[PDB]
Image (tube, coloured by chain):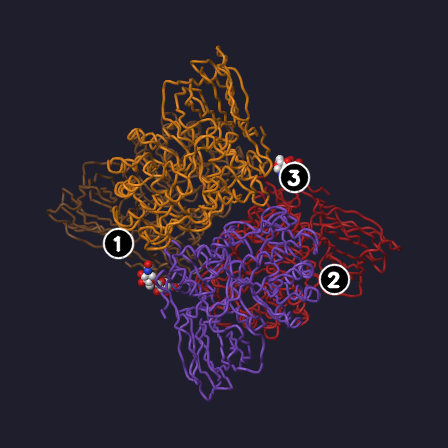
Chain colours: A purple, B orange, C red, D brown
Amino acid sequence: ARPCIPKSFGYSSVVCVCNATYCDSFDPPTFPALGTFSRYESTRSGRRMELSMGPIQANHTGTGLLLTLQPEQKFQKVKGFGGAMTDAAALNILALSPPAQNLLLKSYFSEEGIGYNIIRVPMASCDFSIRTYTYADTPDDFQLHNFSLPEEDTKLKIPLIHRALQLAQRPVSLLASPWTSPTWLKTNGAVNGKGSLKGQPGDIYHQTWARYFVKFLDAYAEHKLQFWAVTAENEPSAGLLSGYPFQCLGFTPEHQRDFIARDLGPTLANSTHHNVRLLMLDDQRLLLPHWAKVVLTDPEAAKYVHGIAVHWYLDFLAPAKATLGETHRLFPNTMLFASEACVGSKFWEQSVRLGSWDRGMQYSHSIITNLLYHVVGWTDWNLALNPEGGPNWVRNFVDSPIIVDITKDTFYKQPMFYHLGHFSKFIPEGSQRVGLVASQKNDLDAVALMHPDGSAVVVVLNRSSKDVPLTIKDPAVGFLETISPGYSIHTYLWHRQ
Amino acid sequence: ARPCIPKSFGYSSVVCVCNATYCDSFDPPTFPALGTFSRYESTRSGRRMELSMGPIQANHTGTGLLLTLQPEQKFQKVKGFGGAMTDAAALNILALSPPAQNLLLKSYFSEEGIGYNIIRVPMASCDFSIRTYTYADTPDDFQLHNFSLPEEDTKLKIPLIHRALQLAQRPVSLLASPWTSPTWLKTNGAVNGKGSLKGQPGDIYHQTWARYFVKFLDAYAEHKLQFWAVTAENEPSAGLLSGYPFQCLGFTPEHQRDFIARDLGPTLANSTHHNVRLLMLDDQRLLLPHWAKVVLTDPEAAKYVHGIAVHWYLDFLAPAKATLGETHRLFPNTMLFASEACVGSKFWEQSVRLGSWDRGMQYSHSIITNLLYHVVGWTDWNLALNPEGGPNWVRNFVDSPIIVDITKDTFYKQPMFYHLGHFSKFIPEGSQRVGLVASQKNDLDAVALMHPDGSAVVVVLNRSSKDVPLTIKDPAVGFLETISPGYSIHTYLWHRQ
Amino acid sequence: ARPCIPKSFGYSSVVCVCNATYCDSFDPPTFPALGTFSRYESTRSGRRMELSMGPIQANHTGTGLLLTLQPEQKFQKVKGFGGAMTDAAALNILALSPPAQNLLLKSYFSEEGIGYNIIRVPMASCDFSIRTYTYADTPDDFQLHNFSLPEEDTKLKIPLIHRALQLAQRPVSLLASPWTSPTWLKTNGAVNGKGSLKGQPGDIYHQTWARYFVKFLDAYAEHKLQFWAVTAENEPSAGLLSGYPFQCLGFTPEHQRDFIARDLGPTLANSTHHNVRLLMLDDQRLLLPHWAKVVLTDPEAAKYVHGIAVHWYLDFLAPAKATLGETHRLFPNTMLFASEACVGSKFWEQSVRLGSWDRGMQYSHSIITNLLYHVVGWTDWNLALNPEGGPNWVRNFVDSPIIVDITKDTFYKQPMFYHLGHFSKFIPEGSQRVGLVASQKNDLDAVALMHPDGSAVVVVLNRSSKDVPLTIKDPAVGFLETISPGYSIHTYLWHRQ
Amino acid sequence: ARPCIPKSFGYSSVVCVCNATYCDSFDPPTFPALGTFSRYESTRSGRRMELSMGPIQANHTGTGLLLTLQPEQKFQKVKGFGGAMTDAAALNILALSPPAQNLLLKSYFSEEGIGYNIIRVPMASCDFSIRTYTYADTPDDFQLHNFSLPEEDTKLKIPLIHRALQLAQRPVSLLASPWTSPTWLKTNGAVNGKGSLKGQPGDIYHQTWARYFVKFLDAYAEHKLQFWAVTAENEPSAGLLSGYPFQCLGFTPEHQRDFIARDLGPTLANSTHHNVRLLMLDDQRLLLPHWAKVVLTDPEAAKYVHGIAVHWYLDFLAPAKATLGETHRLFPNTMLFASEACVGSKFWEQSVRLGSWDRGMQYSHSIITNLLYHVVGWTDWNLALNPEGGPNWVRNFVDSPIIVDITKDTFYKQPMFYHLGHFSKFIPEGSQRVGLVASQKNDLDAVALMHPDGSAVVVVLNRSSKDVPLTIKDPAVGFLETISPGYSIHTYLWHRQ
Ligand SMILES: *[C@@H]1O[C@H](CO)[C@@H](O)[C@H](O)[C@H]1NC(C)=O
Ligand SMILES: *[C@@H]1O[C@H](CO)[C@@H](O)[C@H](O)[C@H]1NC(C)=O
Ligand SMILES: *[C@@H]1O[C@H](CO)[C@@H](O)[C@H](O)[C@H]1NC(C)=O
Ligand SMILES: *[C@@H]1O[C@H](CO)[C@@H](O)[C@H](O)[C@H]1NC(C)=O
């Protein structure tokens, strides 16, 4: 285990500086002895997932805030946590020297880092690309004779993905999403702008597009990568907007329904890759519950949909009950999954603010809200970006948890990285969210889950300046007496056994 | 043989549209009897290298500007003209269907095109690459047992160079230039930023860097490609600026001097590639004559140096006479060559302006000035780019004479292409610049050369809006009465006996 | 009446050009007998509030969509429509020659224009100012003896307001809103950023801030201007955001509640301006119903609150029903008013797009939705801006219905101007929204209101490209057969007896 | 004194943090006792104009670097040092609270700060404005009846200038420069773009423009401000450029000559402001000596020109002797003055790099070069900018020595501020540059001057990483034994008395 090397860039908190020979890391995980609890703490003042242990006590008196575990109120099971291997992310990582590359990948994927188990993979180019390309740019190639993976896949994304999986203990799940089809499949004949697939679901354009998903999976399988899921389209609402500046493909919910029922569903089902799941929407949660109803109340589309993917832009405000809550109500057996999140918009400030505690707080707050409304996973955007928040061919720069400084052969772990890690490190696939009731109103954000083995995990975030004394009660074991300092985040772990 | 198909994109002139089945081209060269001239004319208004013929007459009917050929005043011999096969150019060309690829290469390299006879080849990655790599990225490999060419060379660059040479009637000269060394030879262990070679001339690193040149030449020789020349480093002055964003290797003039004297010269001489020439500088002309004095005043460096390579980018900072003229005067036996003949984009303009007559004029004006100041040859930068000026892993700043639309299997030949061809097509290797005396002050840019066979060539560029009546006198033949239209460029050719 | 003189700037529609001697305008309003209707029509194709008349007859010949007036279903009464006299608007208007100023003011405020009857007036500086100032910048002046109006008020805003009121036949209501207090009343001692009032409700700082409102009203009353209403703070939620770039003053909903209960309410009540109304929130609708619940469920605050002001900017984040509808349901006797009825340029678009039909449609669509969810009035943002969307001391981000070119003594009336006028001109204060039942699902946006005198008004917006045949039934008069052209807005008016 | 409060933003050095109650400052200046020298030192490691004193010794032996004062080799006399009161500068300063504004203005203008005695004042708007305006925007107002100063002058620039002069003990010289004329005086009718004055020198457009200079001066005199000098036009070469993005007015050198001879010269001479001097050029030194020859070899223009104003963009490197030295040689009696300098540019790093030691070094290196080539004064660009390098209406952001953070009511003094102050504080108006010979080639930049009272000043900049032991010999007094630490700058002062 090595501790953070802090560096300030003049914002509210510090980054942790890594290079070819040094990066902060954890010792291997160990469970806390029965009758005791583990606490990991990060603070704006500079603590970074610092470990301590305390006793679980038999008794508690006093009128302080009490959060009581409700182990018999069981909600969703967790799919996992990760981020996106974009062209930008892969280019920045591979521009580091090999030992630094490995310390970066370890940070995210190893048990000695934060245990990511999801990687989102763009199907060809997006805004976080240095050029526009699809896998089938030969005009009118309906048989997809000229489908192929460029160097961006074979030389950047794919070798990094293999390395990530080799470092991970846990099985990693790959999720793919397209931004645009070939331009010759599109009404507007351009990668961006307003335009959808030509023709009507059922037809040659829609069939070719569905077979393009299959060719993609085939090509990745040639390189020994298999996918857990695909989305129907990244942000289908974007292709409905005039002058949309980067790669998109428009679908109304009805077009999405009919494409899935007529084309994508049957095509994937008839392929060797029929086990790959399909997620719909892959867009802002403001489009729910409407989009889910349109798609999922058609049994011919419904039978092909495993889940509903949501995005959020963190610089904007919620509210989750009406969108996430209502969708779960209507379709409780169709998982909700957060497939993309990012910060920076935003407007008076930079795309990358090195050391922003506030941006970290946005991540963990969003993650708790999502977990409180049935969401089974949360996936960050770009795994790594440069200090400008790119590259991005359209200059649509945003922040990332890891910022690579190629000229210095170094990378900075932002507070966002640790805010993410407080969840990803401590909530394996299979974990189930359970009840946690506050004895009184409070300023804390908290969530409780139980590991597949039975043990408990609680994350508590304090976005206020005031320290908050608190007790967590688990009837199986007793009381954890603790304090949540202002501008901190804690994860608590204990056996119930 | 086939005329330009014009298209406007809102700029001052048109591009010529080419695709898989059509591109503008020339008939094989054919020139008239003594007393007749051939004129090729391009105009902002849309003419593109249009041919006409007329008389050279015994009597003088013009009363305006006279330009008199003076074949007895003889200056430099021409090496030739070309452009760079960057990874970006190769990626763009290879994104066309094979028939379109061939029309693109014929446009540049055939006699039915503009007859390039020089190709500059980066040694591994530069900014116009989609990733960072070198030929020996495995560290501590001081004998370079692990030196190898990646796909960029073996799949993209080499095959296209082979195809270029097959199309050219004239022999093509290859010129190589490295941007960065393996980062384990560098002070800063990065591809970019402030950093030079580790240690000092003569040491293990400097000898390893020199051996890399030979390794490069060996590798290319295995692919049946031989080099005319190499430069000592691309823009060595860039690797001295902190945070320099592109691949670089810094050298002060004294470090270049000693590396040449102690390592590169001896190593090259000791190889089977001892015939390959060595050019120094390869940087902005503002660094002259200083850089030339530092290096060429040292006999142990100068015996290994064939010429001085210059870049045009910052030409606006330093006038030709004080730089090019003065260097020639001090070292009249060391040739000057423009190795990156790509001039500076205005800060508020896009990288690519399809159909910009201004950018074309800037090329021809700068070729004329260079010819008037002793320069023997030109390599343009990227032979082709996409409509964004890419791909470039850092940022697009520059235009290119051919722009490829990889969604429409089409490419566009810019005014730059035709301004370049007004020289490259009509000035073969071994042509000699001769005197051309203006009878009075004027605003045209003009230059005269004599082909090896004794025939004359004169280029006349009118950067003004106003038509200029013109007479050209050959004392051996008579008077050519003509008009240089506003915003035009003409190339006149004639037999002298 | 003088017709629109159209000009295109490359966007989907035209602007109307006005200058010192010419501007489009309407005849005095004149309406026909029972059995006849009047129709004003604007189209993307270029029609601008063009008038025609036709029959309402006994026989129903349409077989398509039917919209039936239901005058017995009665909803909210309208306060009115207007825009904001920012420093920027006043600077822009005052840069015209006096005859041009007058045509611009008549365009907005006369019956020969679009009949605005509301002006919102910033209390001191906001982003649309050329400098930061407040009315009491001299520190520790707790009795506000140094409170004064600068030239922005006395030379720019106030004479323009006087001229507006003199031009209007309808009584004009003034609404004031502050952005920041004097920085010495603030926790952070700055005009912007994260900061609130010092101390706690009831103290000297809070009392001084309340007194500032009264001092403002006194000052304006000295210039013979009286206010209809004030808002408690412009965008209180902005001043809780670290680094917020514009003038701001943060209030959580409880702090607003308590400031109103403890200070603002009692101070206004104790003054000679006790009749001026107080509106809460003045912020995004995503903050409702919560904000309304916090403030309005406290009788000590709620007794002082006349209505709830909303901004449209972030409307896309939260549907009308859940915010406006639910707030109405919970607090049906507290009026909803849109105090900054403005959006909100897509992140990749210019602040000003001269002739954008889309931006016009957004205004009319959002007026219609507001009217359908109980909203009683609208103030647009800046009355006029320059072509850069300025002046703004931070950053230009929004368009305006009138754009002034200060170099040509001209102003341009945008499609937004006409989409506003289709409501403002034909819905006087006291008009009541009534039912209008669609016979079948359709894509038009429509709303019916009844004038105080009992005559009918119906606005129909067609946001689609397709013509929609339409009948409108008035049970008292008969059937109006019409067509709503694609990309059109119509206002229909008729007598009902 | 109060010492610097250092803050790092991650760059090579620290900024000094000032706010309403604290700013670093000097004690009143005092003369070093005879037989002693004063030294002020700034270093990248963090020293900021730190004062020490040592002995002047009677001899010296050991052959390290010796700099010998040559007090009888006398060159130019110094006019002064200062910077630009742009709209951007003034809006930033006035957005700080009043006590912080005074500390900022003391930093620059007081003897307890760095002693600026020049302020450059734009005549109306430039790129560092938040809107475009001129003083006479009424079309075809040839009598300039509607000439007036807007708030940018009467409320921001003019009050700050008054306060600057009150703080200064040295007399301050004001310098005015226009960027554009009224658009109706211009061939292109727009504030930016390619365009010059309509008509021909002598005519009404040229006479009105000359009279505009006099009306500007009259209006400033109404406010009790007088000018030392005006320039003929900011950057005349910029208006010759198609698409130039911001305010400009093109003049060829011939046009400038003829405008001065026919219009500006006689008009100023005939006014009450005839004592105001006129500087020509006000543009990049690359335009010299050609522009000087064109203007100054015409006695009808020459009689009106007091000096030549030059600009530099410090991220570029022209040579100086060819430009400055040659112009001095041709026109030794026409002073050379540097009227604007700025850094960044450097696309790949930001406009503002808080704490950049490299950018400070660019300033001091430029000032020494200028002083070594006859230049009598050096004037920075914007006195203060925000952290983005604005406001700038065209987003042409750049760095500034003082960076205002309005949200924190604080300002940061950059290394540039100190590098400038090593000259401005210690080289009063009247100081004459004298000889200083190095005993051996070295990497130091050094310059020697004598104060009006006879005392000596020497600045030494070390841009290398290596400490350099150094002796300075003054025959009147002896030897100063010192060291120039790597990445330092020192000013040495001593009486010779
Ligand atoms: C990498 O970081 C470690 C720990 O801070 C440091 O001691 C070491 O020198 C660094 N290596 C570099 C900068 O090459
Ligand atoms: C290629 O260009 C030629 C000449 O314009 C044209 O006739 C042909 O249709 C083009 N090919 C395609 C597929 O557009
Ligand atoms: C004002 O506009 C009217 C209507 O287009 C036009 O006839 C008149 O010439 C305009 N005035 C000027 C000075 O352009
Ligand atoms: C101003 O600066 C000094 C830092 O040296 C500090 O002691 C003081 O608290 C600061 N004041 C404010 C208001 O931040």
Q: Can you name the residue that lies furthest to the right here?
A: C59
Label 3 to label 1, Cα distance in Å? Answer: 64 Å
- Please determine whether, in this image, residue A408 is positioned above or below residue B238: below
Q: Position of residue B478 (x, y in %)?
A: 46, 13
State which chain disc 1 sits on.
D
- Pointer 2 residue Cβ closer than 8 Å to ligand 3: no
For this view, does D328 lie left or right of residue C279?
Answer: left
State which chain disc 3 sits on.
C
Mark yes or no: residue D218 visible: no
Q: Position of residue B460 (x, y in %)?
A: 47, 24
Residue highlighted by disc 2: C433
Mark yes or no: residue D454 visible: yes
Q: Position of residue C171 (x, y in %)?
A: 68, 56
Residue type of the residue flagged with mark 2: Arg
Q: Quadrant of the N terminus of chain B?
A: top right
For marks 2 and 3 on the same chain, the one whose residue lies earlier in the sequence: 3
Q: Quadrant of the C terminus of chain B?
A: top left
Give the secondary structure at mark 3.
loop
Taking the image in four quarters, ligand 3 sits in the one at top right
Q: Residues within 10 Å of mark 1 (few under 14, many from 20)?
A: few
Q: Position of residue A362 (x, y in %)?
A: 50, 66
Residue type of the residue flagged with mark 3: Thr
State which chain disc 2 sits on.
C
* Circle number at residue C290: none
Q: How many marks?
A: 3
Label 2 to label 3, Cα distance in Å? Answer: 38 Å
